[PDB]
Amino acid sequence: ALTYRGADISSLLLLEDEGYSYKNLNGQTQALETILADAGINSIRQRVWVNPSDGSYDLDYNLELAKRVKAAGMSLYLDLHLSDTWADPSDQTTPSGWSTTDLGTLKWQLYNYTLEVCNTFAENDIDIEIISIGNEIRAGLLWPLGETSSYSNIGALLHSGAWGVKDSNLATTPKIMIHLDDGWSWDQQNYFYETVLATGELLSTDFDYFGVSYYPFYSASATLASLKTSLANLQSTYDKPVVVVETNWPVSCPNPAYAFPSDLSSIPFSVAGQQEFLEKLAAVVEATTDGLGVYYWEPAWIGNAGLGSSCADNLMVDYTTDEVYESIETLGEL
């Protein structure tokens, strides 16, 4: 079994606040987190935004959701976007109110923030298993100070955020993760780490885990073979565990924008395909030296089935009957 078998269900609260309820495999309505817990889901990943004008995914939101994830005995993985909105390689907008002109002030704000976030969970008696300083920061973070035109600045900011959590009041300090997208690409993974560490601004001892996103529908180049190699190299070169923190497989995809990787071309777009992909994906992770696990991204986001992809449906929940799919059980036994 995989050390971590999780899912990111950050949207749960906005959905429930909309009259959405889920039925388990037996047709009985039941708190999604409890359905997942019983199905074997290990941990839950939750995205955190700093100051969204509408409170979406802010700290209050995550505390509400994390109390329930704790209630069900699942571990917690906080995905800090260090932004007021969605952060990715194409957009790393510094939180409103934070500095876009002075790195000293910004390193300080980032340190106080990660520290306050952790201190707030400690106040509520909620442990945090994993915490990522940023989301998919391959193109850096907190622009313009953290643009990749300065891996030195990037290393300084990551170091600062890391120490905010190390210095927090959490009885136990959470595992610190650095998350990059395109996890199947070894050259990009390598280039990023080799570079930022060469600056000496970020130390090997500043973080514990490597986290990578892995999707099959954004490039035929994302074969399981490339991922297996990138995963094995990341681990052997830097000696840190590796986690696939985001992934999806469609139950339906009529017109994909890109061709699916060659070694994934045989898998069907159905619930069974989903089950088959996850197993093939867990095998590669399990076969990797320190492969800790996999997290499915937003399997229950009713209303956003495509989940941003060119495919029609990546959910693990029957969007019509609100009943979870059997693949929920597969994720729970990887």
Image (tube, rainbow, N blue to C red):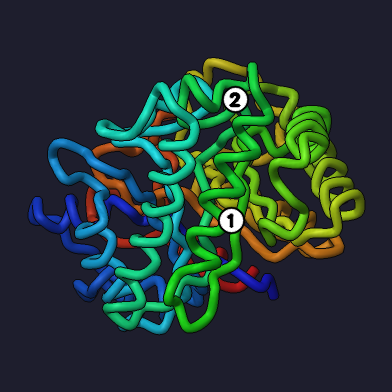
Q: Earlier in the sequence, mark 1 or mark 2?
A: 2
Residue 14 at x, y = what percent? 17, 51
Task: State the image quarter where residue 240 is shown.
Answer: bottom right
Residue 331 position (above or below residue 153): below
Q: Nearer the viewer, residue 9 or 143?
A: 143
Q: Which mark is residue 139?
A: 2
The residue lying at 36 percent from left, 36 percent from top is: 83
Q: Front-most of 269 and 75?
A: 75
Residue 263 visible (yes or no): no
Amino acid type, mark 1: Gln
Q: Secondary structure at mark 2?
A: helix
In the rendered view of the protein, which quadrant contains the N terminus? Answer: bottom right
Please indicate, yes or no, whether residue 176 appears anywhere in the rendered image: yes
Left of 312 or right of it: where is 185? right
Q: Quadrant of the C terminus?
A: bottom right
Where in the figure is residue 170, as x and y percent of width and height? 45, 77
**Is 74 above or below relative to 315?**
below
Residue at horizontal 55 percent and vertical 36 percent from the top? 136
